[PDB]
Amino acid sequence: EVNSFSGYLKLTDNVYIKNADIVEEAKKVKPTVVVNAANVYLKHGGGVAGALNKATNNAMQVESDDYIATNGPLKVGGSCVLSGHNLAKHCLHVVGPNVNKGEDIQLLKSAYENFNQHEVLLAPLLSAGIFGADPIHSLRVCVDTVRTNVYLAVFDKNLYDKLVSSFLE
Amino acid sequence: EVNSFSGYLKLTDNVYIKNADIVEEAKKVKPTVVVNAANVYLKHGGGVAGALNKATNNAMQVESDDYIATNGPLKVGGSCVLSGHNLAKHCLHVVGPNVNKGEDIQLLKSAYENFNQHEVLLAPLLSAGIFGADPIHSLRVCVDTVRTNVYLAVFDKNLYDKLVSSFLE
Ligand SMILES: [Cl-]
Ligand SMILES: [Cl-]
Image (cartoon, rainbow over all chains, first blue to last red):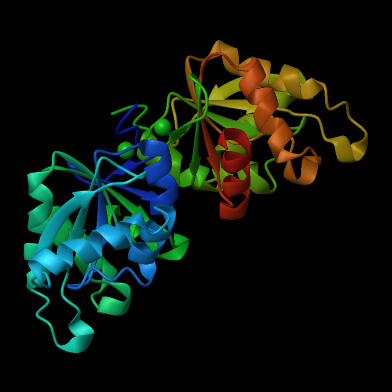
């Protein structure tokens, strides 16, 4: 059955979190929407994007290339809805700003605003890691911007603990 | 409000689990019952017992000594209901077998049977650690024996992951 989220911790009335691998979650949860932490060219070469793409047996990359052929690059802060392949009904590819290449961190709000087009989502934090935002800040922008139901997966235990303790204690 | 368990993962219809510190859980959850992993003399010198006792500012040990003065030692597989102090309404002190001193592992069933006198409990796994049972086995005895609602706290992340993956995958 769809949207079978298990073992999440409520942070706010619409934001939940779990220490988990987003690919394993997608396969068990069968979400309506899984969010990808994308770049503007939808080149799924590492991180969450690479893991999602590999789990789709590269079908996500083939589809993404066809989308770029029609669209050109996405905007920073923008998104597109593509197939969820074997992971979800839909994949919402969202581009957060990459502060390490001089992009504007305020566009993280625009990135998360895209989640409001979907009633429930399985998602990673956006713009952290190689994109240079602080995960604590990214969680805050999510909490302040998303009003639909978001189930966040955080792979790293120490980071998960930092996010939860700082948020709730 | 009481029994405010958050972020647990359902293993069976009545057994739930979380990677958490049982003392921190008791203070946040305000459970009707917290289970102590006790010995027959209710000497709370280490492990969960020492942590619970320290959180009660030693009131648990004072009360326990008074109980032993009246009762003598508990039986292996037995229990007693004492105050929950500042952690819970009640503390169910349960003695699992210590296989390392030649006690009978089958009395782990008797230990968990005591949970059926309580509609909901916050509890640790019994008889593992210094008592020498395998945690995976202890979880199984819990699942097979307890029919009331049990919320298990496992402090160690690697052990938690082993327990959950082996149970559900
Ligand atoms: Cl929760
Ligand atoms: Cl669950």
